[PDB]
Amino acid sequence: MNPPPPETSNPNKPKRQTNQLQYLLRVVLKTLWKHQFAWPFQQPVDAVKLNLPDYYKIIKTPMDMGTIKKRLENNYYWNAQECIQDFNTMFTNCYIYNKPGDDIVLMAEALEKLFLQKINELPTEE
Ligand SMILES: Cc1cc(SCc2c(C)noc2C)ncn1
């Protein structure tokens, strides 16, 4: 079975709208989302349709860009580090689950290269 997805709404979590979080949406997420290799990462892993019955046995902190996009658009975060951590969790899960050198690993690596280039110029907090 699939687990419930990660949380994207929690009214008692305190929230901020900040220039670093705006950059994470307008620059980081949008750059990765439009990439030709984004599609596997645009929603939670569907272990049923993809026939991955061991995925959620191995991966206990699932994360994906559909979840991150919702978190950014719905102002779920307090700070940029929370969102950066979500991207890094997504990449790590892919590398942990998959056989080294598989297509999905090359896809994650291409997105991660762009992620790192954009994070390198995360603006100073205003
Ligand atoms: C090309 C492709 C797509 C997918 S989508 C499912 C997926 C993701 C995302 N991370 O690990 C797996 C497995 N899997 C393999 N190969």
Image: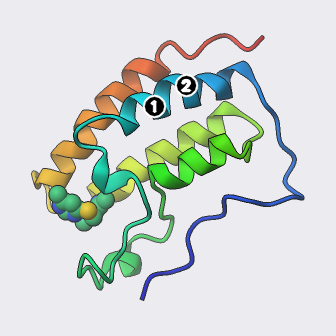
Q: Which residue is mark 2?
A: 26
Q: Which residue is at a point 57% across and 78% down the rendered structure image?
A: 4
The answer to whether the beta carbon of the residue marked 1 is less than 8 Å from any atom of ligand 1 is no
Q: Which residue is at a point 54% across and 55% down the rendered structure image?
A: 67
User: Which is more toward the observer, 63 or 88?
Assistant: 63
Question: Looking at the picture, how far across and down is residue 15, in whole percent?
Answer: 83, 42
Q: From the viewer's perspective, is 86 left or right of 39?
A: right
Q: CA distance from mark 1 to mark 2?
A: 6 Å
Q: Which residue is mark 1?
A: 30
- Are discs 1 and 2 less than 8 Å apart at CB? yes
Question: Looking at the picture, how far across and down is residue 44, in whole percent?
Answer: 44, 64
Q: Is residue 98 visible?
A: no
Question: Looking at the picture, how far across and down is residue 22, in whole percent?
Answer: 65, 25
The quarter holding residue 80 reads: top right
Q: Amino acid at mark 2?
A: Arg
The quarter holding residue 122 reads: top right
Q: Amino acid at mark 1?
A: Lys
The answer to whether the beta carbon of the residue marked 2 is less than 8 Å from any atom of ligand 1 is no
Q: Residues within 10 Å of mark 2 (few under 14, many from 20)?
A: few
The quarter of the rendered structure image containing the C terminus is: top right
Q: From the viewer's perspective, is 104 left or right of 84?
A: left
**How is the structure coloured here?**
rainbow
Q: Is residue 22 visible?
A: yes
The quarter holding residue 9 reads: bottom right
Question: Looking at the picture, how far across and down is residue 37, in whole percent?
Answer: 23, 43
Determine the secondary structure under disc 2: helix
Q: From the viewer's perspective, is 66 left or right of 110?
A: right
The quarter of the rendered structure image containing the N terminus is: bottom left
Image quadrant of ligand 1 equals bottom left
